[PDB]
Every structure is written in structure tokens, then in C-alpha cells.
Image (cartoon, grey):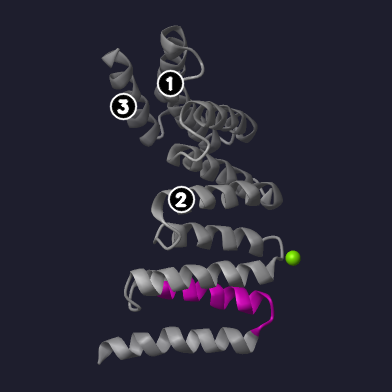
Amino acid sequence: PARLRTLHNLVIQYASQGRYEVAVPLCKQALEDLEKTSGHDHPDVATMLNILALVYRDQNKYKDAANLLNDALAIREKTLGKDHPAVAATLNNLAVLYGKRGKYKEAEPLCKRALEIREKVLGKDHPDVAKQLNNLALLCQNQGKYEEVEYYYQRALEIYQTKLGPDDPNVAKTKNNLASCYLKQGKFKQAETLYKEILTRAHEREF
Ligand SMILES: [Mg+2]
């Protein structure tokens, strides 16, 4: 009923205040009760599982967080669609968890799938598709895929520069990331050229 709607906002309120003492039981309650209502395979079951998984991730219960997210991802894929936005959202959460836990190789495919969903949903050129590319490029940097890192950061910059103005802060933030990647990979002459472009537009603005 609407009791599930109220119970949901209570789990958010206490988890946001870092009060998992209150948040976890209310979430496990909502979960137990949503199973009696419409079974395990329901969009809202995944919605609750997703919140509880984030609560576990923040509680450093990394192993358990992953099982709830893989559970939610499967429930979403079956009940919403393999290319549904909520499926991409769960995919991101998982890649974030794997990436934070140091498993970049295992995280990369989930992030690349989440990008494929965001492209279908928001269009091949979009400032969220360009946001997702900066995450994916960082993931490759932590592996040594310097060829992929340049390509992803560069495609994000192209989206950012055409969709948002060249003086947008994401243009400089992305250029700063590609610039720092080039330093890592010893491409010092190419990194300096990028730092000159970021500084010259900043100087241009004052005039
Ligand atoms: Mg390679």
C-alpha cells in the first residue's frame, strides 16, 4: 500500500543522516513486506535492495552490497527491460563499488554497458554521456589502457564543447583530466599543450 511509500522515505531520511541503526531495519522491513505483496521479482524490491546495498557499501560490507546490487540488476533487467535507465543506474553503482574496492578490470565492463544504455536513452552526444565517459576513462587509466583513456576523455570534451559553451567548467575539468593522464603516461609535451589551452581561455575570460 501507501505504507510502503512512507516506509521508503524513512529509510532515505535516516540513511542520509548516517543513522543505519534506524535505516537498515526499516529497509529490511519494507523488503520483507514487499515480498508478501508482489514477490521478489518487482521493480520496488530492486529499489529497496539498491538503497540497502548503498547502506552496506558505506558500512564497508562490500561483499553483501554487491549481492544486493546483482540481485537488483537482475530484477530490473527482467521487470523493466535490458536497456532501461534504472538498469544502467544499477550498473553504475556496481562499477563504482568494484572500482572503489580496487577491481578495475571487473568494473570496466559494467561501466561500458551503462554508457551503452545512456547513449540509447539520452542520445550519442549528451552531457551525461560525456559525464559517463570521464568515469570510464579513469577506469582505463587505473589499468594502463592509455590509448583508451585518451579516446574516452577526448570524446567527452567534444560533447562538452559543442553541447555546452567552450567556457563551461566541464570543458576545463575534462581537459585537466586528459592533461594529468598525459603526465602519468610520460607524454609531457602533449600535457603542457593542454595546460596552455586551459590557462589561455581562463586569461581570455578576464578581457
Ligand atoms: Mg590495450
> In the image, which residues are magenta?
171-187
Residue that appears at 50% across and 85% down: 195
Q: CA distance from mark 3 to mark 2?
A: 31 Å
User: According to the image, label 3 marks what residue?
Assistant: 9
- In the image, 119 versus 182, the foreground residue is 119
Main SS, magenta residues = helix
Compare marks 3 and 2 and give the one earlier in the sequence. 3
Q: Quadrant of the N terminus?
A: top left
**Mark 2, other Cα within 10 Å: few <14 / some 14–19 / many ≥20:** few
Residue that appears at 65% across and 61% down: 140
User: According to the image, label 1 marks what residue?
Assistant: 27
Q: Ligand 1, what quadrant?
A: bottom right
**Mark 3, other Cα within 10 Å: few <14 / some 14–19 / many ≥20:** few
Which SS class for mark 1? helix
Q: Looking at numbered disc 2 in the image, what kind of residue is underneath it?
A: Lys
Q: Is residue 68 magenta?
A: no
- Residue 160 falls in which quadrant of the image? bottom left
Q: CA distance from mark 1 to mark 2?
A: 32 Å
Circles 1 and 3, Cβ within 8 Å, touching? The answer is no
User: According to the image, label 2 marks what residue?
Assistant: 120
Residue that appears at 40% across and 31% down: 15
Q: Looking at numbered disc 1 in the image, what kind of residue is underneath it?
A: Cys
| Residue situated furthest top in the rendering | 36
Which SS class for mark 3? helix
Give x and y (percent) for residue 158.
45, 73
Q: How many marks?
A: 3
- Residue 67 falls in which quadrant of the image? top right
